[PDB]
Amino acid sequence: AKAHVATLEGNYSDIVLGRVVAFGDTGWNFKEVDMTFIADDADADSKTTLFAGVLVGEDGTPATAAAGVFGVLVDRKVLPGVDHYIGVFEPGEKVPMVLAVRGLTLNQLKLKYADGTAIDAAGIQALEAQGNQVTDKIVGTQFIGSVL
Amino acid sequence: QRGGVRQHLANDRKKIVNLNIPFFPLDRSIDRADIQNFREFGTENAPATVDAEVQ
Amino acid sequence: MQNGDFQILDYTGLISTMPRVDTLLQSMNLFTEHFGRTTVARIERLDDGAGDIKAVQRGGVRQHLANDRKKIVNLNIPFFPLDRSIDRADIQNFREFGTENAPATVDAEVQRHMARIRRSHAILKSKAMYAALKGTSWSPDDPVSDYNYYDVWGATQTTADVDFTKLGVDPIEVLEAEARAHIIDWAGDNGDNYEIVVLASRQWFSALIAHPQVTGAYSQYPSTQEILRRRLGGNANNRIFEHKNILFIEDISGNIPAGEAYIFPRGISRMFEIYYAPSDTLRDANQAAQELYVFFKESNYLREAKIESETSFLTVNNRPELVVKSTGKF
Amino acid sequence: LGVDPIEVLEAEARAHIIDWAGDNGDNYEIVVLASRQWFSALIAHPQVTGAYSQYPSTQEILRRRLGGNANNRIFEHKNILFIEDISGNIPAGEAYIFPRGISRMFEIYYA
């Protein structure tokens, strides 16, 4: 009775609205950190809980508070529709993933803590203090059922 | 204002779904005993024929 | 297609389901547009008059005449930007949605984003133009360009109210007495055939049609528009209604506040206007302006692309004294 | 009795339909399907009959049976079609409203 369905909403360029193209070192804006992909305790084939836009500290631990906010997870393994990585890894193993750090414009509305709650008004300083522009002037989009 | 922060655009949705299908049979048979020795209901003395039963 | 490695499916099409955008008032072409060179505009007024003349005995003293008015005003124009980018990760290893073989391409994303930009700008222009008819500039979240044209010129609203709980009072006669007399007196020309048009919120319009003083007239013998049997205006989106030589147009766009309607005449010269200004780039800075600018780019290092769009305009109501703000009690 | 039900029905159904059509308000057409009691209550409302008591009309619901001697008691009013469903599949006291012409709204598959 529960017809199988799938959905897609957003993509990589919907979070990183703008980037400063550094000359020579094209990776000037990113860092690589090892993170626990599959939860330490979970089913052998349980999907990872990481989602794009989650704040992460320097050690790869998801940021639960403004204190531990260092960067935003951006790696390709966590983008929507990339579920084909399920089952490849094993619980407790740490795999590198790219983080965005500096020289970017970030959509605030898609930045959330590890718990999924919206970014805090204090944690925004850390990202902005890193040399990034956290912005809210997003046009947005409206679908059927809205008068235009 | 002329010089300040700019604005950005949103994106669309691409939902997908699939469904199943059911099946329905219906069968019947006939036997000699139902035809040979019964008069047709619509006539005085016409013996029943298998064709009417099939139809 | 497949529903797994070892067996197949039947894939049967795709849906579009795009929302609707209204264009009612844009079709009427109320406005005239002037392409400027800067972010400031000048307007001037020159009012003439006449006077009474008494009787004086032959000889004696005489009587003399008097002079006329002059006035001048200035304004300024806001800015409306919009941008978006695209990156490598947005198109690698992705199907082109709707087909089960083709891979994603970089051209389709750009075309779709351009379409969205065009739609958004059209919607902006429609909304801002709607705002002018009410008697104010648009300038949302930009307190620099909030102009009350009534206050800018020094006119008055002249709110003609109608309370639909009074069955014994005909709303059309109140409309005549309060609005049409004012319109006729304050036209300023010597032409005498103005057409009166009413643009009303859906609630006010529907409440009007139910009034006994209006339904009574049409109920006793057949009419061309059987408003009491056949839906007004046919099956069209919005109900057009004719009555006592006053064209009623239903507004379903959902921006006119529910309970208000605005009464204005047609054909009064230079009553509605919009001015454009050039964008802030060295190509256009201080040069002739254009409606919409769109810049497309691709980094020569070949790792992302960018799309930009800009426009700046202001909508003006030169004769606010000729837009009567209605209201409805319920 | 102080409010015409057709007005509420329009304000709800047409308002919902025009916005959720998905393409454009290209002169849509509405259809109504209702049970026996709902149909009878609609016809018996004085605000409906008041529009036909004064001068003649095609249907003449006051003197001639709607839809003629045939079944299904069809009826049209204010460019809206009403049909009486006698099959019994429509729950008692209920009615359904949907527009014609919408593409891919209904489909049937075979295996």
Image (cartoon, coloured by chain):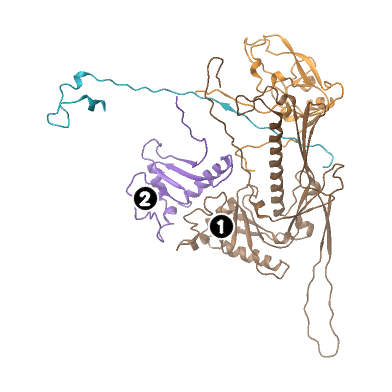
Chain colours: A orange, B cyan, C brown, D purple
For the residue pair A128 and A64, the one nearer the viewer reads as A128
**As drawn, which residue projects farthest toward the bottom?**
C58
Circle 2: residue type? Leu
Marker disc for residue C297: none
Is C281 positioned to the left or the right of A118 in the image? Answer: right
Which residue shows up at 48% across the image and 54% down it? C230
Residue C130, image x and y in percent?
69, 51
Which residue shows up at 68% across the image and 55% down it? C29
Q: Where C196 falls versus B1 (above or below)?
A: below
Circle 1: residue type? Phe
Q: Secondary structure at mark 2?
A: loop
Q: Quadrant of the N terminus of chain C?
A: top right
Q: Which residue is mark 2?
A: D66
Q: Residues within 10 Å of mark 2 (few under 14, many from 20)?
A: some
Q: Is residue A69 among what the camera can see? A: no
For the residue pair C291 and A70, the one nearer the viewer reads as C291
Q: Label 2 to label 1, Cα distance in Å?
A: 29 Å
Marker disc for residue C241: 1
Chain hosting mark 1 = C
Q: Secondary structure at mark 1?
A: strand
